[PDB]
Length: 264
Length: 124
Length: 133
Image (tube, rainbow over all chains, first blue to last red; front, side, top):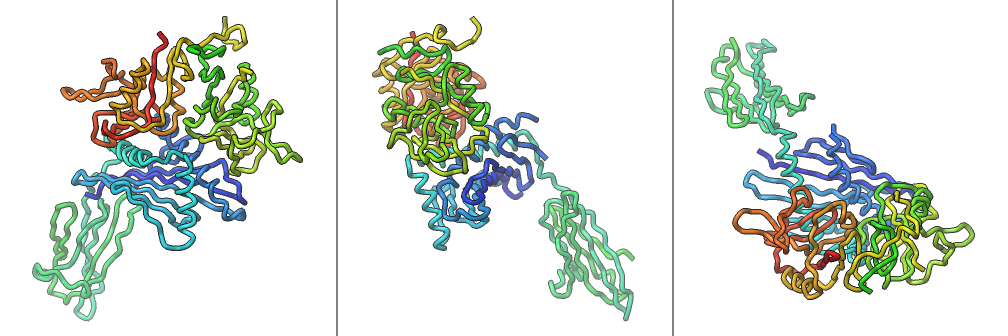
């Protein structure tokens, strides 16, 4: 099981030096879209989206003011983004970071576990980084405490969401179907399909007499989204006619080992 | 003095000035009108010492500071000049109105953009 | 009679220390000298006051607009798990959202009606409060 994740993606915009009234926050829960919020409201995909609305509107305002301390380009569209993610792992240990993007490029990162700020090396990443850290120094009460509270905010919100039981990581085990085709030159192709499965991680390969065939003696489907929240893949190999009973499709998914022979 | 006042019942008193904060977002004009309707005006900043509580205000709010065409200077609703070394003014959005923020900052906004706002009665 | 807001309906805000914020029969003051919770508690008591108690969203609605984090008068009880104020009052049911931030037996106030748990020994700004008799 992958960890439980919470992301907040905040975007402010500038046209010809002028910071726009709008800002957009995308909230994602366990990687799935969960909320879209503008200046006025959050919306799902009831009106107890008040908490998220009061909160994420404050951050938008702070980031409107932060952008105002960046007047390097009075020409064109420009974006500033504040992205905070936290995770709860299976061991019950936690991850938490915050990243700033300008025109879609990263310039400042903060790991909230280890209290460690990181810059990229480009002269551009650094002028933006410092601009912002300076604005923070400027009596803007960006105390050590602010960041430790953001950390514990993201994690507490995650717990609250998890507890309301909103997005389940339910297992959906694959439907498997072996097929035969290209009956020629005393040669057959056998194909093993797995479809309708979650989660995405799956093992699927042909065996001769219980031994896995090399990767190279085997053709490989990608792992495609089914377009209903699940996945499909396949794997195939060429065998001599009359050797069918020696060849089996072996699959592991979510602690379930299964073997599928070539139907006669 | 042990007593702070005269103020409306239910207004914040500090050094005999009276304040109230409003969360219903309004443009500068609707904001100014609302304050005056309660025998007040938008926040005027005349003193770092007497209005030192403004350092602990979160977020940005309409104050009563307006820019005049062929003026270049900023002035209050009441026609007062803005006193020097009280506020740092920052360009944020093109406009002729200013949001208050900590610490003694004015952020320029379009007068038409809805925002939270602070009323103050002058005790003069 | 009805809410008019004219000079005739103006009162004075009940007795407080000189130069404190008076609002709805409460007195508040903010202190920018960083101190641990104990030095903070002692400082408030030295001015015949206590640390911030939060008992009402309506009566203490000014606390929604407070920047940054400050010692309030909330202390942890070992036996059960629950919090209580300096004065022995229970913490009322739906007033504060409490966030585990650091392991500790004291709480920092932050807007909007949040308590962040911190180590009682960590220096912080603080808010004193006195009820007007």
